[PDB]
Length: 71
Length: 75
Image 1: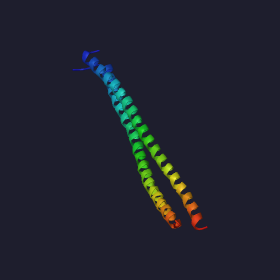
Image 2: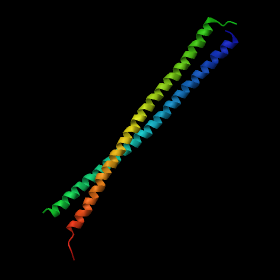
Image 3: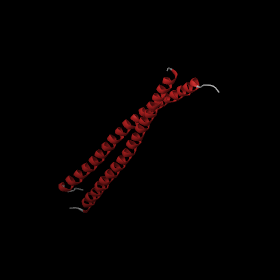
Image 4: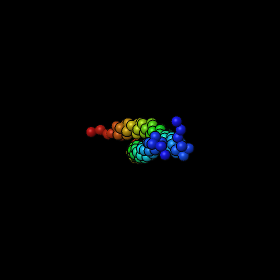
């Protein structure tokens, strides 16, 4: 084959290997971002469930106070 | 100036493979990105709810304060 053809084939083989490496890196990183945000969201869901519990415990305190007033 | 058919067939193949890799990559990134914006959206929701419920809580504390004062005896 001609020398100019071999160089172009070689160059494209490189760019394809380079590109497959870029895909692996960009995917790894976007999964890493994904795991950070889904954990952030889990912590938020937990803050809300803890707040719901504090709220539910005050409902019961309210009841005990009503029992003292309305008894 | 000519090149071989086999060579051209091989350059074109690689050029196609390279553009497809770029395509595959763009659309996997796009699917991540749309799933992340969908998630940052549920986090916006969850936070508005939290603030809403914090308000219920703050109002229960005021009611508790008022019952403690109302029941309070002298001396």
